[PDB]
Structures are given as structure tokens and as C-alpha cells.
Amino acid sequence: PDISQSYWTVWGMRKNEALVRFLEAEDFDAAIIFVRTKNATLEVAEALERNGYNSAALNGDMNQALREQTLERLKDGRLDILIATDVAARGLDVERISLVVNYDIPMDSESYVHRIGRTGRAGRAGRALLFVENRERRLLRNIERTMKLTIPEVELPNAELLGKRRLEKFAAKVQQQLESSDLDQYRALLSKIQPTAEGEELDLETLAAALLKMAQGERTLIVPPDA
Amino acid sequence: PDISQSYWTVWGMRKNEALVRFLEAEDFDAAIIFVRTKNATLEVAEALERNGYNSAALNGDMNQALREQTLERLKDGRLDILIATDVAARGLDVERISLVVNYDIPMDSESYVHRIGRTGRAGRAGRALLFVENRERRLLRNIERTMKLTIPEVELPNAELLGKRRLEKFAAKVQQQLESSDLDQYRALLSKIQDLETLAAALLKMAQGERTLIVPPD
């Protein structure tokens, strides 16, 4: 019945890059990204795709066949993220949605409320994240009195946070590999991998660091220092 | 032009898994796989691709621009394997083909010669490999007779040889990462995961990719 709401002040990076950071930064089942216009839905969708998420745009004038296809692909898990306008998302009950992103802050403050109500609609608790430009403080205040709540401000998730999130999911794949049965056959190959021709010392720790680098996913475990 | 020729009696595994085995076992640049049915043109295709190769069909029903685009993708390296029928391959020429596989035995000697000729061009060294089912040995003997020459029989590349190949390629990738600049940053992350040897073995399993280094027998 409850939605946890926060907002970020657009400061350090553009909205696209921040969205990817916020998505990676904490767990979500499915998410809906609300934007001002159809053109925005396409720019978001392409940023999310060149960052490794399965997402699609819902638009008010889209083919009704594609709408039904897109909505069920979200239900069965071929999609995790929809990018929608207020027009397109009316009539949308999808229980996977655990995260609502107000990518563009609305002027109508009850558009805000109807937007974050696409989650927490179950007995489950969901989350809502609002992007606010400094130019837009007035509409945040509008929202924050239209409902008597103050929306707490979050910071942009930092490199160290993202590295820890990546390490923790990587460690979970490591753990399912240790439960393997053939693990001992792999132990015997460790000595066989190593270059002994120019300067030899079977240095297990240096080998394992090379193997970690080769085993890490596309999301590098060494996140560049900033932000 | 030579062009060493050999043939495999189809035995103990199906032609598709066997082709994957022969492809891994020896270096090739680009390869062309000759089949008879243009369904096989398409099915061998994504047998090769689910084993990680870049391959495309080349059949009589996909023309004439899509042909010549497919060949240029083969020639510039965006593809490494064409699966062709004889019709769709009257016009040659790619100069990357070092391997011709007669996946389906030709119906006559002249066809076999034609197919072989796609390699060994510009006088460079090339290889031809023929698949012969038991029931087709007449066809093979027909080809051998007409041609005045026998084709050497070869064994399936065995599991140990495959393990050796996969290990060799992997250890050369490992060496590269052992000389990379940022390695100490990764060194510090080992303690944070949850003994070294056990962790490294599991990392090896995750780093090796799809070509598993532990090859089961056969």
C-alpha cells in the first residue's frame, strides 16, 4: 500500500546517464519511466538499450497490436522497463512494476500521484524516483504540497556504490559455481594455464586476478573513479 | 593448387557435431560448407552459430543482391563460414577460403572437383574435408575411381586434442590479461568475494567461456 518516494536534483550528469546509475544502484523487478513526450520515450529507450536493459516505449498513438505485444512481453519478462507518457500509460495495471521514475516532472501534480500509483498497487512496497531540474523547483514544491509530504532528496549513486553492487552480484555467480561437482578437474588446470617460459613462478594470486578480470561481466568491477 | 584432401566416415556422432569438432581442431581462415538440400543450408547454419561461429546460408532462394552482400561480409571478415548449395555458388570468388567441407557427398567426381576448387586459389595452401556415410561408400568409390586417386581417411579429432586446443587458446588469452595494466586493482578484489585455489578454479570455470576446457570423453 506504500510507495517510498525520493527525488534527485539534476546536477552532475544528464538524465539518461543518471537513470542508468539509479537503475543499477538498487534492486527492482520492473520499472516504468514517465516522460513528457513521445520523442523523449525514444531517446530514453535507446540509452537504456545501449546500456544493457530490455526496454520499450509505450506511446499513445502506437499500433494497438504493438501495445498488447509490449505489455505482455513486460508481463512474461522479455522486458523489464517501459518508457511511457501519461497518455500511453492510462489503463495500465502491471504487477511486476516495483519502480516508477518521474523522468520529466509533471506540472499537474495529480499526474504525479497517478504515476507513482502504477506501483505499490499490490500488498508489496514499491519505490518512486523523481528527477527535478533546478529550473523546476517550483513544480517540486507544487507536488510536495499537493500531497502534504516532503520528498527526500537523494544523491547520485557513486562509483564505489556501483562497484559494490557489481561485486555482490558477481559473488553470487561465483557461489553457484563453487557448488559445482567437477571443480577439482579445474583445480588441476591452474598450473597448466600459467606462462613459465620467460619468468616462472606459479603465482596463484596473480593468476586468480587475471581470471577474475576475464570472468567479470560486461559491467566492469573496477568502476572509474568519478563520479 | 593443393589442397590436401581427406574424408571422414560418419560414425559415432552426427554430421553437425562432427563438423563443429573438425572446425575447432585445426586453424582455418574462412570455410565453405557444401550441402545438397537448401534446408540444410539453413540448419547447419545455426548449428554453427550456436557453437559461436559467424555463418550464413547461400542458397538459390536469396538473390541476387543478398548473395553478393553475403560474400562481401565473408570477404571483409564479418562472416567466416558460408553454407552453400552448388547452384547458389556457380559464381565464386572469395580469397579467404582455406577450408572446403563436402558435408554432403557430391553425386559425381566433376562436382567434387568443382567444390574443392573454391580453396587453393592464388596458389595458397588449402584443405578439403569430405563426409561419407556408410550407405554412400559407392558414391565415394565412384569419385575416387573417376579421379584416378584415393582420398585419405581420417579419424574424428578426439576429445584430448580438443582439450589441448582449447587450453592453448585460453592460456594465450590468460597471458594477455597477466600483462595488463590494471591487474593490481583486481588483485585487491579477491578477498572481497565469498581459499585461493578453490576460488581460482571457480573463476577459471567462469572465465573459460563456452568452449569448456574439461572435455568429456567422445
Image (tube, coloured by chain):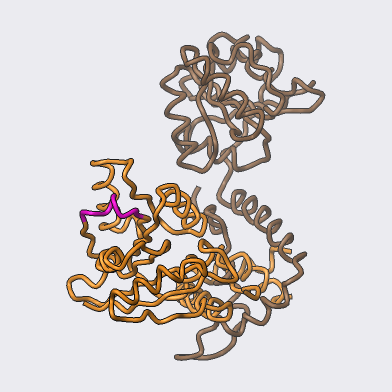
Chain colours: A brown, B orange
B38 shown above or below A63? below
B41 left or right of A123? left
Image spot of residue A96 (x, y percent): 70, 29
Quadrant holding the N terminus of chain A: top right
The residue segment tinted magenta is B84-91
B201 shown above or below A35? below
Residue visible at 65% across and 26% down? A128
Can residue A137 be seen in the rendering of this structure? Answer: no
Q: Quadrant of residue B198?
A: bottom right
Residue found at the very far left of the displayed protein: B122
Camera-side residue: A95 or A146? Answer: A95
B135 left or right of A165? left
B123 left or right of A129? left
Q: In which quarter of the image is residue A102?
A: top right
B183 left or right of B104? right
Residue visible at 65% across and 13% down? A114
Camera-side residue: A125 or B116? Answer: B116
Image spot of residue A195 (x, y percent): 50, 85
Image spot of residue A82 (x, y percent): 56, 27
A19 inside magenta stretch: no
Q: Quadrant of residue B116?
A: bottom left
Camera-side residue: A182 or B113? Answer: B113
Count the numbered circles shown.
0
Residue visible at 65% across and 32% down? A30
Can residue B195 be seen in the rendering of this structure? Answer: yes
A145 shown above or below A153? above
Image spot of residue B27 (x, y percent): 39, 74
B124 shown above or below B114? below
